[PDB]
Length: 58
Length: 58
Length: 58
Image: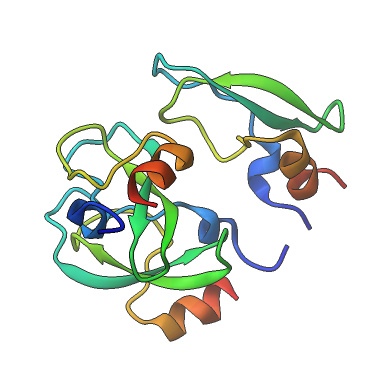
């Protein structure tokens, strides 16, 4: 495998109102994508910048 | 118009914690992509299958 | 070498819809059919046998 399993988790905005720009790795598209995150909870496939997403999820 | 305006809304897991793998239209990528929906609330850009998303949002 | 989730048991979860799916069974060294109920469960959960085999079989 080329990346940790959490990179394969679908985007989760968490339960807070969606307000913040964040990034997640989309394994189907093989790319890190912007989404709107609530700021609280969610899952490990959640990065502050595209660069950090790309470093972790390759 | 190619699709309803609601197709451009962000993915929204909502405030509940019943994790349903679901699909949303990503207008940037022009693709129906997977996200976690929490089972309540959220918005109209929320489909039970990729096929339903692709028919409704193109 | 393959994802950790390949080693998790099949899990239909508690929801009451029907998504025929495949999971990897390490004892059998093959992917096997199960019904996913639509929510919860785990990542050892594929729409096609071929994807399950690609990801989880040696």
